[PDB]
Image (spheres, coloured by chain):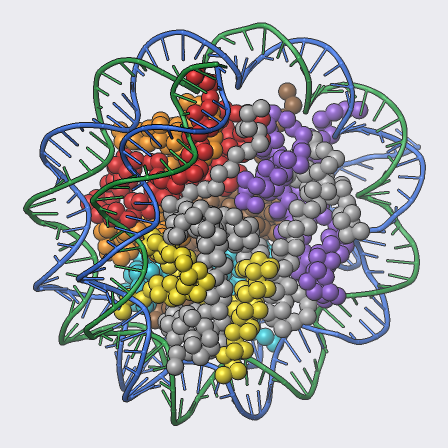
Chain colours: A yellow, B orange, C red, F purple, G brown, H cyan, I green, J blue
DNA sequence: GAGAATCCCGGTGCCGAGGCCGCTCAATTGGTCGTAGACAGCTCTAGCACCGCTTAAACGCACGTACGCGCTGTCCCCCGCGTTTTAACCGCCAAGGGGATTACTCCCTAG
DNA sequence: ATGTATATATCTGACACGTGCCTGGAGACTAGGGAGTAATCCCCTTGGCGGTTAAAACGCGGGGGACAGCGCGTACGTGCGTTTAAGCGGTGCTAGAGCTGTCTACGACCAATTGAGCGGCCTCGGCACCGGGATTCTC
């Protein structure tokens, strides 16, 4: 299958803005955007895995990486939402 | 030869979308010089990209990963 | 009726309002064709590629002309000269 | 049944897990890391989509154009300093006129 | 008094290393503020690397990586 | 008072050698205090502090070379804070 | 019997192969790629060691100070573009004074 | 003690091979040690991404060949690809 | 006070943006084991802090002169506009050369 | 009266070579699946038609903008008196960096399965386009 992320952010957009649409050129723009941030944070996860010789990537390493590359209050909201997401994973 | 294709009103439109009010006559040849060296650098990336894959076409992925290589990447044509 | 300049203000307002390309497609792909045939022989191209370098060229032109606009404002001048774009490329690290 | 619905997320855990597995970033990988990256991506496109909706509502448009997402990135200075290196195709720039150029 | 800890003749030597012949008197506070926000941006990455390393002190390689981060790679 | 000769010898004497300009103990507390902003009583390191010293010296000499080049552009040797703001804004920030 | 001596090269080929295995770049590594890495590395340090040597006999010193490699790296445009963005500890400034800034 | 990894002796005696009567200092060994692992990770990454862009799952002489033909500005690549090809032919000769 | 040049309100195909079914891989679940993260515990390097002599570097006041700055006369070179004319672009038609992929295979790189 | 010139004589001071050692790179053996090749279908783009048409080239009137030039003041450079708190260096103390041991549970691997997102197809209304009237800087 040819992987993409169309129905995902369509569901997300219906969750946040249930009377707003988007175009296919913009859909490709956000596809390039999600691939860019995914590749950036995965390269960061690899390099600060490689800095302290740790062969396993856990949540706290890339947590510190998103404290690194993201600026302040976005990093605070991201780490709060991430911590509540992994605690509602590990609660179940 | 074929370097005057970006002629004077095209550079005038680029200046008007860039924010500069008054234009002197020496701006045009300098702007097309930096354009023909910048696009030369991008095509210089693209030739090694094409000859690496043994593939003789240049797609939008080629120029998008090349803009990723010089750190001026663009969204819309893959990531 | 006859003005020194007010049409330029409406033109820059309309161009900052609009988002359409202001560079003609045929001379652009002609010049990248000449560069590509100057480098190698018998290359193939895609259309999405040449609108992608059209977007890259217009973004780089917008950035460089914003740079020359700020440099001319700090030089206390209205008319732009190639000294400003030369210092802009020297400061940004494009040439050195 | 899906791990995204199990953790309450929307972006899938298995797809991004395969993405971080075959992309040679680490030989040994985690399991809270894919759900946490899904959470971070959910926050990122939530901020992006709310900014795009704000840029589309005042212009009275039911659809979001690349001009609207360009207005969404170039307005807030936090995201502007986050992703300022990346240009936007058919996005343009905001109308900016300096104070010297104003005729008096 | 951390702002005025760094001396004005040190900024004079930095200007003469940069190649400045005539320098004004109001440049020092603005130069100090730009240097303060630059070193704060560096030491933010450095202190997140110290919390990365399970250490309560700073070292060499964290500052090394913090200099490799934003594109002023240290040599 | 002899104008310009002593300044020229001064310019040559710190464009020839490689001496340190920023004193080690003021900058020490400076970065130590910037550190306290994140980590208080941060045990520090000598390699860390001369890393910040050489990084700050390189950034200062790059910004000041940018400033005096754009001042020589502006037909005036002297330096204003708007020149530093222009260099910071054009250079990326 | 060493593979570096079999390749005729001086920079080691087993060391870069070891660093390529656990360096997490590719899951499969060819035989000639570490040799090619050692070759381009030997060429790069050979070129700047010639540059540091002629800077050392220009200043007439038996020991290459890092300042010697500063005016060795700032005397060619290829390494002025390859190492222009880099920042060097204890590097100084090359002699460069504008003609207009000089008096008379 | 710890077994530190450094190629300081390798650069030291190519310096001795090409300049038989020239000395060196320990700060210099640290400084081009920083050079050679800087370029080692830079070009090891480049080839990596490239090959992954090509969707190939390995690293032979081809990917690194186009990476070193593409990466550095000039001259050193022109001698480098020739001397590297000559190196791999003495390897395959042996 | 007039006039090009704008903004605004109403009709019009249309053609490119929302559903829907088919279904095929891809995410999900369960078992197994061998190793790496984490914690406890261990030895000494090195960072922190304070005392005291030396002193070259730094502050501060005094003045002097070129240089930043204010104003002015001037070519003069860009700016608005009428007139050809010359290449851009749209609509379309056929080719054929090149991109994808199926399908075995063997060797050379993992271990 | 004093520098000095050119060799001492001691005499430290920073640098390159001769022994241990240990551990990881090399030789040898096994496997399997990743490039290698190539054939075939299909698809898109490079030429080539031609009308027509917004738009560039060219020349001309005109008006503020850039050029050097001259004077007014003052601000940074230079200097000496007076601190001062940087530098060396020394010593004393103890946190914490770093290495080792050991355990055990998260996670890679493998086999079966179910389900949901990709896509061709279908359908329809938002926006650009066009036409004409109000409105606002500018002369």
Answer above or below: position of B43 versus I77: below
In this picture, is F77 found above or below H14? above
State the residue in front, J16 or C77: C77
Which quadrant: the N terminus of chain H?
A: bottom right
As rendered, which of G31 and H13 lies closer to the eye? Answer: G31
- Residue F21: % across, % down: 71, 46
Identify which residue is drawn at 36% across, 40% down: C20
Residue at 44% across, 65% down: A15
Position of J78 compared to B63: left or right? right
Please state if I12 lies on the left or on the right of H23 as rendered: left
* Number of on-image labels: 0
Say which of H68 and F91 sits in front: F91
Q: Where's residue B34, x and y in %?
A: 40, 35
Q: Is residue J113 above or below residue C56?
A: below
Residue B15 at x, y percent in the picture: 43, 32
Q: Looking at the rendering, which quadrant does residue J50 occupy?
A: top left
Q: Where residue I15 appears, x then y in whole percent?
A: 23, 48
User: Which residue does the image show at 64% across and 20% down from the upper left?
Assistant: G104
């Amino acid at each position: 299958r040819k992987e993409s992320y169309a129905i995902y952010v369509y569901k997300v957009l219906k969750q946040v803005h249930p009377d707003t649409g988007i175009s296919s050129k913009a859909m490709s723009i956000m596809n390039s955007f999600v691939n860019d941030v995914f590749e950036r944070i995965a390269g960061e996860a690899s390099r600060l895995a490689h800095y302290n010789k740790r062969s396993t990537i856990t949540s706290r390493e890339i947590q510190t990486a998103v404290r690194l590359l993201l600026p302040g209050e976005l990093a605070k909201h991201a780490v709060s939402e991430g911590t509540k997401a992994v605690t509602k994973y590990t609660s179940a | 030869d074929n370097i005057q294709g970006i002629t004077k009103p095209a550079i005038r439109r680029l200046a008007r979308r860039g924010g500069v009010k008054r234009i002197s006559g020496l701006i045009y040849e300098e702007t097309r010089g930096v354009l023909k060296v910048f696009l030369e650098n991008v095509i210089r990336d693209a030739v090694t990209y094409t000859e690496h894959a043994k593939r003789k076409t240049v797609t939008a992925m080629d120029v998008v990963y090349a803009l990723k290589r010089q750190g001026r990447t663009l969204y819309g044509f893959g990531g | 009726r006859y003005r020194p300049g007010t049409v330029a203000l409406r033109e820059i307002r309309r161009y900052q309002k609009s988002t359409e390309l202001l560079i003609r497609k045929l001379p652009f792909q002609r010049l990248v064709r000449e560069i590509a045939q100057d480098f190698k022989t018998d290359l193939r191209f895609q259309s999405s590629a040449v609108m992608a370098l059209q977007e890259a060229s217009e973004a780089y032109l917008v950035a460089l002309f914003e740079d020359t606009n700020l440099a001319a404002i700090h030089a206390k001048r209205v008319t732009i000269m190639p000294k400003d774009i030369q210092l802009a490329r020297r400061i940004r690290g494009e040439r050195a | 049944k899906t791990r995204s619905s199990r953790a309450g997320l929307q972006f899938p855990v298995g797809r991004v897990h395969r993405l971080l597995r075959k992309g040679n970033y680490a030989e040994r990988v985690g399991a809270g890391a894919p759900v946490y990256l899904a959470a971070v991506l959910e926050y990122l496109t939530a901020e992006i989509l709310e900014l795009a909706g704000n840029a589309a509502r005042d212009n009275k448009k039911t659809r979001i154009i690349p001009r609207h997402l360009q207005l969404a990135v170039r307005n807030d200075e936090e995201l502007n300093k986050l992703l300022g290196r990346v240009t936007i195709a058919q996005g343009g720039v905001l109308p900016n006129i300096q104070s010297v150029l104003l005729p008096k």
